[PDB]
Length: 11
Length: 116
Image (cartoon, rainbow over all chains, first blue to last red; front, side, top):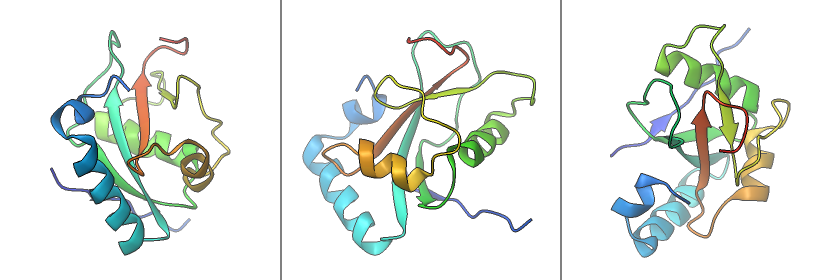
């Protein structure tokens, strides 16, 4: 399938 | 290891994909996440994750917790090469030590803390 990119949220 | 992803994609295909992704995103690590066998815990809709190197294992725990819709009370444990990685380690350190020959990092998850 496709890749799930992750983005950390800022505090 | 006992991962379904390795039984649906041959090694040559996985290694080629892993080498390109590590070139396209040198600040990210490709991670394959699957449920450990005999585990009693919810499933994961997607198993391929591109994770920033500076994300900690504790932050990935929480991210995975939400995708499974686990409560904060419910247990969740990661296993890399049959060892539970420390929550204070980053995904970059974990990848650098444990990445397999296809340039993927493999993580199993379970409700149990004992290998398993």
